[PDB]
Image: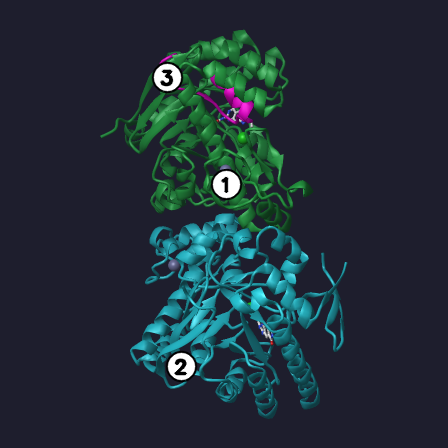
Chain colours: A cyan, B green
Amino acid sequence: DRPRFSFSIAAREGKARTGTIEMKRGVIRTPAFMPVGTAATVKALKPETVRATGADIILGNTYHLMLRPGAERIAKLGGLHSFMGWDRPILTDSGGYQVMSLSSLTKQSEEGVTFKSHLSRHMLSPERSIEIQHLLGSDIVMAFDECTPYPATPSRAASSMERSMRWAKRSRDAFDSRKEQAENAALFGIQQGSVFENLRQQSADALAEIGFDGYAVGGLAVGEGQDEMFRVLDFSVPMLPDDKPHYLMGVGKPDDIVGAVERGIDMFDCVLPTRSGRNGQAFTWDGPINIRNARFSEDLKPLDSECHCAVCQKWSRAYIHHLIRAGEILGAMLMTEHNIAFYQQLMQKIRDSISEGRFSQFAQDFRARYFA
Amino acid sequence: DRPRFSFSIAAREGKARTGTIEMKRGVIRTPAFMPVGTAATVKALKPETVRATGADIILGNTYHLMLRPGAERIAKLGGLHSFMGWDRPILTDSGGYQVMSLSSLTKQSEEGVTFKSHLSRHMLSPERSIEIQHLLGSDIVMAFDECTPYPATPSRAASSMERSMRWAKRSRDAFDSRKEQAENAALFGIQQGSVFENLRQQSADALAEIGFDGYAVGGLAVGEGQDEMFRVLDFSVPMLPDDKPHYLMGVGKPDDIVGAVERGIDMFDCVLPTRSGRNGQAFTWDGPINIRNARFSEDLKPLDSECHCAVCQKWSRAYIHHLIRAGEILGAMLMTEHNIAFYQQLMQKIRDSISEGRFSQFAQDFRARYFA
Ligand SMILES: CCOC(=O)Nc1nc2cc3nc(NC)[nH]c3cc2c(=O)[nH]1
Ligand SMILES: CCOC(=O)Nc1nc2cc3nc(NC)[nH]c3cc2c(=O)[nH]1
Ligand SMILES: [Cl-]
Ligand SMILES: [Cl-]
Ligand SMILES: [Zn+2]
Ligand SMILES: [Zn+2]
């Protein structure tokens, strides 16, 4: 039987790595892209379709699930895996980011965050976050953190990061005090420190002293732009333990993913393929297209000329254009399946190119064609 | 190779019949239920899923397709079958009903109907209707008719029926003058006459003199109620040729279908399973349920206890309740697949019970449990 958690690096090129995470519920090929399951569904896809695209693991939003249908309710029904019908690994976020971005009213303190839902008063703390993630039956549990707004002054970035590190220790202890969770799940810590190298180093040191199964680079993709995100990754990823997975949450566009892998990132999640698919944006190897545009009304070609997904095997741009213009559910279904499949094909090409020692060339060829 | 059209009756019980329609694109088992493809999609289902539920044939709405994406455009793209990815028979309606129920402004005359779309001025006539259905590549073409509003005075019902019969002859001649359509498709005529036996007889006689591949009972399910619909069917169906299919369009609830089969109907279509599925109504052998209701929030049972569909094999009422409450696309997908599968299972039980000479008992047992 598979272990609780084992990360193994099979090949490397520069800072990029390819390998596997073995967990009780399955193997995760890295670098990995996680489709986002907001409220117990990857929007517009059955779980079998998510798997057919190549996904090994999905993400669930703790903030949404604790509000609807409720964490205790999901536990009573047998956990998130059986509730939604996905039997493979699930990573749950902590709630610490969405509580601040999505709540109408919040009160922050050293204890945690109290908030009002957009749909009653609610509470999130390191302890409650770890508990909710346990009730959901999460395989990869995220420490409860604070995502510092950008831009941040050095003082505010430091104060925020320091609180996040105290919360990381509380998250570790809560997780370890629940025997079933400690034996069957993994716990990742989240580095903070905004764009400041010294704070990033202090955060990495604090997380490594506590000890986690994996390490995320938090606090990025919050308005700083790709140049600055890459500059921060340049010095931040090498601070993390080499032998554990490196996770960049909330990223991103295809070129963001490629450059982040070049900088040592092993795991990603983003709503872009699902949300923008529903809005009519399709990813192709020649860049994104907006299927709503009139130029596609009689285009018999598939969304992408090389894509192997079931949507591209069968339906035309012209048909999907009609569905999206008409507001048809099938339009959302087909666009989402293709976009998630495209993202998985990107990850497969990244993995294979690292394994063959030609990732640098792949990245160059990818960028030249995608931005032509 | 299959013929253009062959209807064969394999077994009978009272007025009920079971058999097959063979056409170039496939075999249709009768009595048959046709899921409705409004604008080139059975809403929220891939065509493979429609087929997996047991459907042999789907319906397409001429009124919608001529407005978006357009009949000539669909023809240029290769026809409706390849456009939407359904390779089996498609029955198209004539447009004569939806033009009057859905248009914002209409002008009726002996030539046809001019109208304004809810999304420009447009025109429908017997000739244009048959042409549109040809451009779509329809397998079963419907004569262009007028559905008399209910209630109707004898004078107005007679005038409307007489116009419909003149339009039936024009539909026949238009269809026959297009060699490719006449050789590969079938044409059904539509009986009118409101609730009046003498007008129904005159209409049946006119249609039989013209000659069609099948005959529909038009002008029902327009507010008269089940008792009156059944009373009209009692005398109307025996007026039609016994050796051709009998089609009751726009019907209906499960009990409407059972009683209509008891009265000699072989074919049905209705938006009820799809539309009401998206709205949270699920059909069960114990009657419909509203999955939005709070009583289902922790119900681990499938939608129906006996249903063999993929939704009932995997997901709980509690999960689907959550999806529908949340407005999730997957909720619409799962409810629709189950409801269409339920309707197909109803048709299968009807067919099998007629074949075994126990349809009367099935109808009694069905009604006792469904309305308990
Ligand atoms: C995935 C687990 O993350 C957490 O528990 N906290 C967290 N979430 C983030 C989500 C983000 N999304 C974006 N951009 C779209 N940037 C993000 C940063 C964080 C973060 O610092 N911390
Ligand atoms: C299916 C082909 O029908 C036509 O071309 N004309 C037509 N359509 C109808 C649709 C109806 N839907 C309902 N109730 C929901 N009743 C209907 C009657 C007709 C009709 O008389 N004539
Ligand atoms: Cl995101
Ligand atoms: Cl209907
Ligand atoms: Zn594709
Ligand atoms: Zn079912």
Give the CA separation, mark 2 to mark 1: 44 Å
In this view, the mark in front (3 or 1): 1
The kind of secondary structure element at disc 1 is helix
Which of A274 and A36 lies nearest the eye of the viewer?
A: A36
Q: What's the residue at 39%, 79% (across, down)? A: A17
- At label 3, which amino acid type do we have? Lys
Q: Which mark is residue A16?
A: 2
Number of numbered discs present? 3
The answer to whether residue A324 is magenta is no
Judging by the rendered image, the residue that carries numbered circle 1 is: B312
The kind of secondary structure element at disc 2 is strand
**Marks 3 and 1: CB-CB under 8 Å?**
no
Q: Chain of mark 1?
A: B
Q: Is residue B126 above or below residue A63?
A: above
Give the farthest residue toward the top.
B198
Which of B202 and A367 lies nearest the eye of the viewer?
A: A367
User: Is B54 on the left or on the right of B159, as rendered?
Assistant: left
Q: Which residues are magenta?
A: B242-262
Give the quadrant of residue A364: bottom left
Residue A7 in view, yes or no:
yes
Q: Which mark is residue A307?
A: none
Q: Which mark is residue B244?
A: 3
Mark 3: few/some/many CA within 10 Å (<14, 14-19, 20+) = some
Which of B248 and B62 lies nearest the eye of the viewer?
A: B248
The answer to whether residue B244 is magenta is yes
Q: Does the beta carbon of the residue at mark 1 sit less than 8 Å from ligand 6? A: yes
